[PDB]
Image (cartoon, rainbow, N blue to C red; front, top):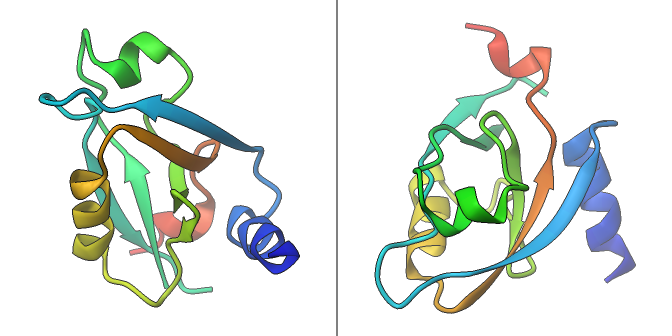
Length: 111
């Protein structure tokens, strides 16, 4: 369990991390979209376009370019594909806990 905290620090690589909870409405979603970016050091899920009027938007904390490190205690490690990440996000009901890192890193900008 203390290992999870380290796993996150490793993913964050010195980025500011934050955990927060959002209530997903019974219909509408959290109100943001994501994209996968490959590093070299595997893959990250990054917030793209926060929908106006959404929980995500009205909550005010989440931002474009942040990386979702965890969802409801599940670290988004190599264990699962980017589409599996999205599926988890989509299938999550009610209070969703996200662990976030602020912005991206130069590693994800390599092509």
